[PDB]
Length: 60
Image (cartoon, helix red, strand yellow):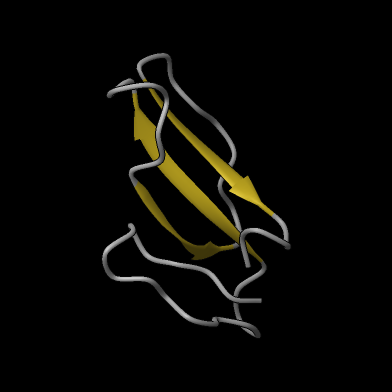
């Protein structure tokens, strides 16, 4: 249950209270992640900016 916030800040671990991790970014250089954190509801998306939510492993 360890995740990172954004990238240059990292997060460490945020178990209990939360439920999964999530990242949000848009077209930049070659499809890269921009922000990240652990929450519980992260559905929906858009078209130029995508925001997904991971469960565990490689992301909380």
